[PDB]
Amino acid sequence: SFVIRGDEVRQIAPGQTGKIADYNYKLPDDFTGCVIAWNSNNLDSKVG
Amino acid sequence: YAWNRKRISNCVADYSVLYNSASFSTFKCYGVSPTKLNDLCFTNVYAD
Image (tube, rainbow over all chains, first blue to last red):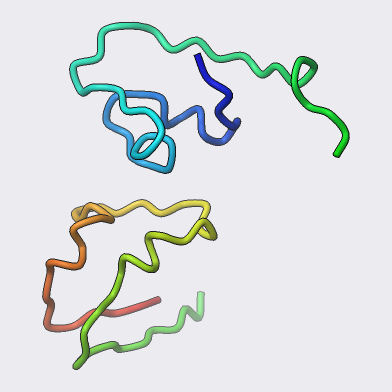
């Protein structure tokens, strides 16, 4: 489970490359699973 | 419609700085991985 950014979500997938995809988390090419994403602005977005 | 073309040649290129810039929203390369780009040498590079 992650805190990743919205524009970033695309990166949690097999082939992609990018900031998170390289340094933070790397899904394998062969990945067998699902990627479930839902923005939780309410839970963690405070003023400031 | 007017698109400008610039000719770049006779030098050495550091593309990694370009890749390692947070500044570009989209950096998609068709044919080169953005990394390992430093390894290539070309006759003429055109920038639009």
